[PDB]
Structure formats: structure tokens, C-alpha cells
Length: 163
Length: 163
Image (cartoon, rainbow over all chains, first blue to last red; front, side, top):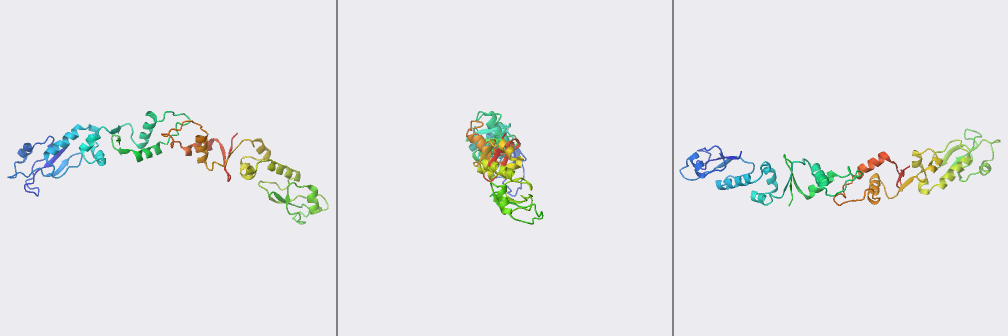
């Protein structure tokens, strides 16, 4: 989980291929003793990674630990679905802005359940007469909430990006 | 409108074919002067009719005027749709029993309009919240009323045979 194959720019063609996997936190001198040096300093050749997100080929290791600390900052159900949540967003501090603004639904599993939750148990309208009990179009209600609300269908539930 | 070709049983093979059309009221002596006689009395050979209903081949002319008076008794929108209404019933005095029991819908044109009328403007449930405004399945409501109520789809509207 969350480990990188990063060495080295010396013998740029992935010659001097060393340094297998580095879980976080990752140090300059730790990897430097892992690899030696390439007679100078041209290292952390990002070429492979077990990460739940998208990383770049020249990201500095301090930025990597920064990203990891932002990952470890977030709750683990969100850490499981970072791939889905980052589709709406573009960065993690951006995600850390509205990290309070996520509605979690383990209880709701499709849009129908979202409609039934926000109508029935929320009580967004009050009266459910027995003459009117069946007669609440959860499908169209979910269509209209899908038009309005930013929704994300995931494995562990449905995540509503409300602002 | 409502006229019969009735003559004669004398020369049974529609020989002595006389008497073109007879609008109501229709008299024995009026048709008798129209046709003469067939040396005896065997007449009103019912063979053709402009009538909005089904008549028989040997119906007496007094019964014909009786049927016409029952037609003229009824309102003209029902006189226009006697063909549809008599499908549920079998006779006209039968229809004159429940002639008070017909719900007329020029306003409603399909089953959807029937559901929207009996829900919205009738106020069969009261509250229509804006969170619940769309969310009234008129289709299923019309299916359930179609299961329960006797409905007839016509040209001028929808006629509900309620008891």
C-alpha cells in the first residue's frame, strides 16, 4: 500500500536500476543509502507506484510525503475512494477545502435509496398518507437530484458533493 | 338521423319494396298510407336503419317510438355516445336507471388527466408539497382506478360509470 519505485536518473535508461519500494515516510538519505549515488544528485526516477491517485514523474519526495500526510489526514473510507472523489476535484488541498462537504451513504446504494432516504426518513415533506404512501416517484426524484446535486456512485456507498 | 326503411312482409323477398325513411314519431297509418297494404297486415319489415344503437328485425313501431322517446329523454352528449355506453349495459331503461350515475369528462381526455383531476383539483389528499409536487404517479393511479372503476373512453371525453 502506497509505495514507489524511485531510482534513478543516473543512467537515464533505467540503468543503475535500484531501490525497490518505499513506503511513507520517505527520506532523501534513506533512499540515498538504498541506492548509493550516481556520482552526482539526479535521482527519484518516478517510474512505478502503488498509490490510490495520480502522481507525476518528477515529483519531489517532500511533496510525496506531503501527499501521503494529506492521505493519512483523510478518513479511510475516503482513502478507499480517492480515485472516484478526485474525478470531481483536481488536487487534495482542494479536496481538503470541502472535506467537510461530503455526504456519505453506506445506507443508500443506488439513486432510488437516496430518494427514499431524503423523502421518508428525512421527512422533507411530512405527511405520507396511506392513500399517498406508494405514490412518490423516487425515480424522478432521483433524476432531479442527479440534475441538481453532484453525486458519485462508489463501492462503499454514494457520496454527495454538496456545497 | 334516426330513420328506418320498414316495408314490407308482403312479398317477403323485399318485393313490394316501398317506404323510404321514417323519422320519429312513426305512425301505423302514416306508414300504411306510405305503403298501401299487402292485402293483409304483415308490414314493418325492418331491414335498414340510421339509428345510434342496435335494433331488431321485428320490433313493433310503438316500441320504436318508445326507444326514440328514451333517446330524446337522454342528453345529447349521451345520445352521441349511446353506442359506447350500451356496451356496458344491455337496454335503455337499464341505462335510465343509472343515468344519474355517469361522470362526464370533457376536461379529462386520457386516464392521466383523470388521475390528475381526481388528485389535484379534487384534493383527494390535500398537501402537495413542492418536494412532492412532481411525485404523484398518475400512471399507476390511473391503472388502479381502471382496475376499480368502470371507465369508457369516448370522443367527447371520458365517461365513468360509478355506481
